[PDB]
Image (spheres, helix red, strand yellow):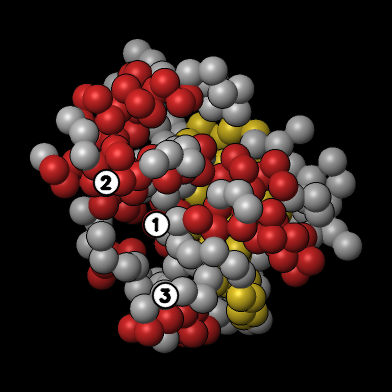
């Protein structure tokens, strides 16, 4: 019964991208990037099952999530279409791509946004996650959200979203609740389960920020372990959270355009 949902993130010429969602299952963290890209045609994201109103919430295993996302991406994926992802979305995207190849569908490449193949480590905990994750995605004062009761922090996010035409269509009180619950669930995925375990036979492009702790910075090169063909590393501005928001996302977009899009 349950399925993931393919969502169009932009309004012409160039390759496509299908983004896999990070923890929480939403595409909304890619909207700003999608709006800044100029070298791509169709940009989609896969939305996890169970985030819509009146739907049954779904808490998939990592493998189940990959399956949901593969099935959804398969409608548009193939020649001329990248798979991409940020944070846990990068691991999902890697495994999604391997599943498409196994089914005879070959994406143009895999775009990894600033995660190594080793996934990085993560009541007051609930509020901190809200503030640092979707609070970040929404350009919010993260320190102010932390100093708040969970329900009051949630209301500030809704106040910010409810008349923003980029997200007001779907980011309701119910959607936010479902996102936060699925996020907590997916934040418990085991690092050993999401680690790549085979080589991927399409090119990989890794876009990495340069303000990581050294112990994380030295883990990016391991993407080459999982590349049966080309792997390319591209430095981008910002840090892990702010690279997908203004002003850094415009430069991230320019670099994706240059390295992966249509000249």
Q: Earlier in the sequence, mark 3 or mark 2?
A: 2
- Asked which secondary structure carries label 1, the reply is helix
Q: Nearer the viewer, mark 2 or mark 1?
A: 2
Q: Could you tell me which quadrant the N terminus lies in?
A: top left
Distance from the alpha carbon under mark 3 to that under mark 1: 17 Å
Distance from the alpha carbon under mark 2 to that under mark 1: 15 Å
Residue bearing the label numbered 3: 212
Can you give x and y, in whole percent of width and height, for residue 138 in the image?
A: 47, 38
Q: Nearer the viewer, residue 47 or 39?
A: 39
* Residue 85 visible in rendering: no
Residue bearing the label numbered 1: 88
Say which residue appears at 79% left-offset and 45% top-offset: 41
Q: Earlier in the sequence, mark 3 or mark 1?
A: 1
Q: Earlier in the sequence, mark 2 or mark 1?
A: 1
Say which residue appears at 13% left-offset and 43% top-offset: 124
Say which residue appears at 57% left-offset and 35% top-offset: 6
Toward which corner of the image does residue 236 lie, by quadrant? bottom right
- Asked which secondary structure carries label 3, the reply is loop
Distance from the alpha carbon under mark 3 to that under mark 2: 19 Å
Which dot marks residue 129?
A: 2
Can you give x and y, in whole percent of width and height, for residue 154 in the image?
A: 30, 27
Can you give x and y, in whole percent of width and height, for residue 230 in the image?
A: 65, 81
The correct choice, above or below, for 43 with respect to 231 in the image is above
């Amino acid at each position: 019964d349950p399925t993931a949902k393919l969502v169009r993130l932009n309004p012409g010429d160039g390759p496509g991208i299908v983004f896999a969602p990070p923890a929480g299952g939403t595409v909304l963290g890619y909207i700003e990037l999608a709006r800044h890209l100029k070298g791509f045609g169709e940009i989609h994201g896969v939305e996890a099952p169970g985030l819509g109103a009146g739907e049954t919430p779904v808490y998939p295993s990592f493998e189940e999530m990959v399956q949901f996302c593969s099935d959804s991406a398969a409608g548009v994926a193939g020649d001329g279409v990248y798979i991409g992802g940020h944070s846990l979305g990068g691991h999902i995207a890697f495994y999604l791509a391997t599943m498409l190849l196994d089914r005879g569908i070959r994406p143009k490449g895999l775009i990894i946004l600033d995660t190594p193949p080793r996934l990085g480590d993560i009541e007051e905990t609930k509020v901190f996650i809200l503030a640092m994750g979707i609070g970040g995605m929404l350009d919010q004062d993260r320190d102010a959200l932390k100093d708040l009761p969970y329900e009051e922090a949630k209301q500030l996010l809704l106040d910010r979203a409810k008349n923003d035409p980029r997200v007001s269509a779907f980011l309701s009180e119910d959607y936010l609740d479902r996102f936060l619950r699925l996020q907590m669930h997916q934040l418990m995925y085991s690092r050993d389960v999401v680690l790549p375990q085979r080589k991927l036979d399409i090119p990989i492009h890794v876009f990495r920020t340069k303000n990581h702790a050294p112990e994380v910075a030295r883990l990016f090169s391991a993407w080459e372990n999982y590349a049966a063909g080309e792997v390319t590393f591209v430095d981008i501005p910002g840090d892990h959270a702010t690279m997908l928001r203004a002003p850094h996302v415009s430069e991230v977009a320019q670099l994706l355009d240059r390295h992966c899009g249509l000249p």
